[PDB]
Image (tube, rainbow over all chains, first blue to last red; front, side):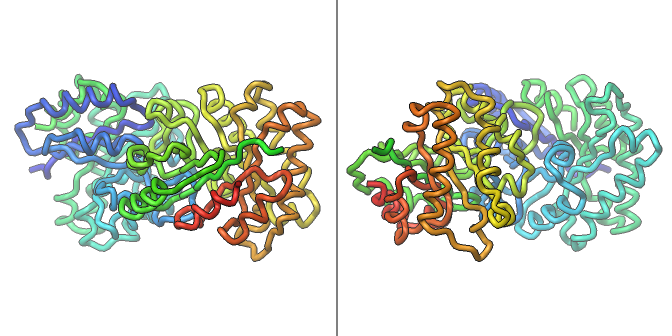
Length: 249
Length: 249
């Protein structure tokens, strides 16, 4: 059995009014006949356009990032401002933020906890780099990451967490991940949850894959045992995203 | 003579729909009988609300931050997305970003240049810390900062630049800046522009003060020779901001 799958569009730092309104239009015309939760994470700027125009009832909108408290933090957006704006989903600890914007395990854990304390649904990203994969440190790394997040949550909190596995080693490295490798990483995450938190938490937990998914490979990836959906990059800006959602049947 | 003054509200990481719509309402009811350019810099989230509801023709809206190019930079907003959204003003290199988010002189300079290349009006922030003020390194520091920005611009570009002086040494340190000290820092900036760029550029350049301004001290500060307005923090969330604008007469 699988828990309810998730198809999440990570638009990243992209979009214009025209192009995004067109995409939201396709989305609104789409028949989604099964139980999938579709999630659109736009830039802070486009949240209002998005919120207003996406009318399809299988789609929720999400923010790509946030900080815990409001205040003197010029240029940043806090969880409280997001909640007031009526945004209940968030992406946290994405690899790009970990690589470029100084987010350590500890910072991610803290944000996830704040988000969780305020009532958000979080997609928490984890993943190891090339050097880590190569020296055979995959399990150590990913589990070290998960445990940092886990260290801040209560068992009940897991109901609001969704984990996304990013194969950093294969993103921009000229390396390629196979479905089997994706499965081997997700099975590692899920066993840890099982032993450490509980087979109850472990069986309900969604684990999304966040490597390269396109409409061609999506189905083979979803077919794997421990894959519950996708955190999609590039293809989420294309009509092809529709094929990715259909792949979670 | 003074160039046209600027009253800039830096809302920082703050605001809710209700409180901000109330504030924008006061702003819309306000008689501003002289030549001042009022600038409201809200969070990325509130840009649309702001843009829609501020109808007063002496006010422009601005973003608190941005990165140069669109792309795979989860959680960030680029200049091109801002322009498409119709935002032509930006705050860059604010002290909070320099202290917390890794912005060096060089990063600031690059952003200012991109912004300028795309047609924005930039308020570029500069300022020295306590340690710097204390060891008597004020001139070295500030001028080092300005020169980094200046190194990337063409003389014509100065028409889009506004400089804000932040007395970092006096922000959260328990130290207090006097109007005379503010004047001594602005005169230093302006002389540098004069010698280095041209007395033409120097005489048209707005230099805003960005320390603590409230409605009580604003007039004494504006009275100084080289002060052309304010980059206001805290008081910009209060009705008192109206008194600050009136102070630039």
